[PDB]
Image 1 (tube, rainbow over the protein chains, first blue to last red):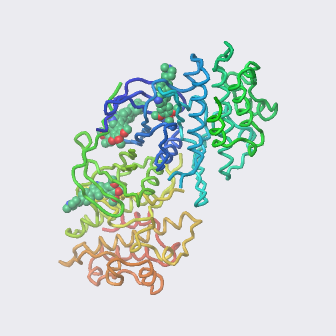
Image 2: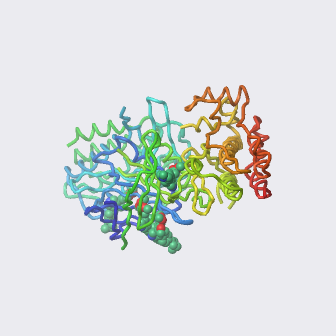
Image 3: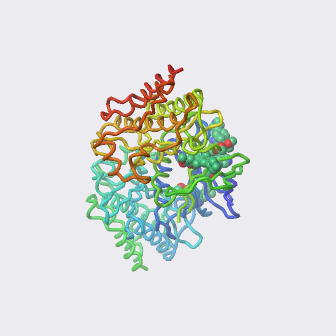
Length: 292
Length: 281
Ligand SMILES: COc1cc(-c2cncc(-c3ccc(C4CCN(C)CC4)cc3)c2C)cc(OC)c1OC
Ligand SMILES: COc1cc(-c2cncc(-c3ccc(C4CCN(C)CC4)cc3)c2C)cc(OC)c1OC
Ligand SMILES: COc1cc(-c2cncc(-c3ccc(C4CCN(C)CC4)cc3)c2C)cc(OC)c1OC
Ligand SMILES: COc1cc(-c2cncc(-c3ccc(C4CCN(C)CC4)cc3)c2C)cc(OC)c1OC
């Protein structure tokens, strides 16, 4: 049974479209890529061939297809479906308690450490476009990371670095200083893990804002909402992050709450301009496991 | 908002080997060919899929792409048009040719190969096949052939040893020059032309089907077996006396010799082979 019914569009953008569909009686998500993003479809397909990629905090693969008749080509990725949508969607109109906030951020840290750490199997993987729209919320209150179209793979065992062929760059708002100033060391796998850590810090900030303490919570805002235009350019982001050395502000009410005080410390250790100074995904996971 | 019928019935296995399996299958009442990749040959699915993701080749003498499917182990399928007559290798075992059929076969292969080789601007990158042989050519009902298997193809697993050019066997191939890969294909084309020409009847005479170098290497030749024949002794396939009574086989012997020069830069181009074949008969 291979047949799929497309039922409703849950997303349309430059990337193409995502549909909720039905397959063997279950909801599935069906991404139809834009022709402009053909290199992402192939990269994501290479990533999902990985033996041991499957993980509770990585979006589960079902199938990938490239189909063509005559001069047109369709590119399909079929995954498990998450009715609750993306973390971006979820944070807009939900506040969190301590337990739910830590469950979300530990789950993301768990998925990211799973990507970053080689299994001797699965190569080490850097995501390169981590952000709240590329994280889905599951009914158990954990998240899963999505969109492996820009991912970098590395094997320490065979000294192989696979940066792939994709002129796509990460989401501008979430780019690390070394991406925005284009000094990043492109032939160095660790460089790409460190870009993920920067973006993780920004996602931590977005989530923490939505955790209630002492009857106070912040409204949902995207990173750098206060310092860049609504639809920021590459240069707008370079200005604030690299020229102005800006980082998201920590609300002072966080310092009254031990959990938010711990998270503020953890997101600052993701935001060093010096990429070597940033925490590892494993260290972040261990720290969040210790926090209550 | 719409049904996507992806179910492909696998009806009969038409090929099994180190590559995996090929099946005749059915989609929506329509025959398709389904190549199911072995783990051994997984990189061939990725290379061909990357090529078709870059350029959707469409040509009467190139096997028609339908789909690349990956299903979670991982199953990798390549789906193409189905040619019920099977491969040129299969076809030549039993079938003899007349002048018209022989020329139609070899001009159709040259047409496909020139299409791969040529860069078109606005179009397609230049493509070298890197495993051209009679098992990678399918026969169509209209008497033309199509070139199959772009799993080793390069745009601008090793080739089948029996068909490797001398510069591949002696490792002198100029790997920095894309033209080097075009010249390796032309060598293999000349061996295919010899295989076909042997089956063309003239004056009541035909040769039995044999693969290239059948009389000078073992059934399953080593790399070294091939290097000694092709590079050290500089042997070439035998041209039988009987061909020189037949004007078509006389022209085809000249053509195949111009594909087999030791110096890769002396070999004819696919475009010049086409021009030569349009002036025979
Ligand atoms: C993969 O292969 C096969 C596919 C199909 C098939 C099935 N549904 C829809 C389509 C289709 C419709 C419309 C467009 C275009 C039309 C113009 N513009 C508006 C952009 C969109 C593209 C595609 C096709 C091509 C049929 C086949 O055989 C009959 C195939 O071959 C086995
Ligand atoms: C990020 O990337 C991928 C995501 C998905 C995916 C999987 N489950 C659920 C969804 C979803 C459902 C529903 C909403 C709602 C949100 C609020 N409002 C009601 C509008 C709609 C949002 C999101 C998506 C988008 C599939 C993908 O590929 C098949 C993705 O690409 C890898
Ligand atoms: C995912 O997988 C397989 C799919 C198919 C297949 C089956 N029905 C219809 C289609 C179809 C084609 C094209 C459109 C177009 C229409 C307009 N345009 C602007 C957007 C999209 C829609 C639908 C396809 C591609 C066949 C398969 O096997 C032969 C598949 O598996 C490999
Ligand atoms: C070379 O490579 C590929 C070839 C094909 C392919 C396409 N049409 C038809 C065939 C075929 C059908 C039938 C027979 C035989 C069966 C027994 N009978 C006694 C004579 C006839 C042989 C061959 C094949 C093998 C598909 C591929 O991929 C999907 C290939 O790989 C790219």
